[PDB]
Length: 85
Image 1 (spheres, rainbow, N blue to C red):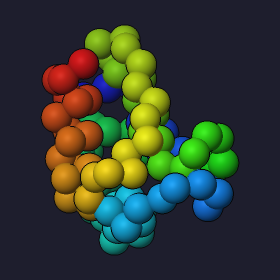
Image 2: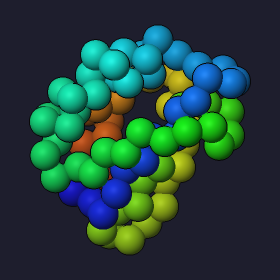
Image 3: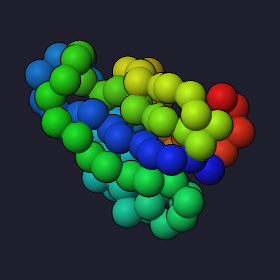
């Protein structure tokens, strides 16, 4: 629903299991779940799990999604990116 999603990950600061879940368990699944969702796993940048989005709405998103769980992040991605922002 957008131009790009770049998860900035790393292991450095506050992280989550929901994030981790997404990262491992849900990665290939969100890649298939949201076909039109560019998915790049990125490295050390800020705290830890930020959601970079650069939508085709042409808006920015770069945010610590530490508080959200595996499915919910992927669905929230769809929420946000296919038509939240």
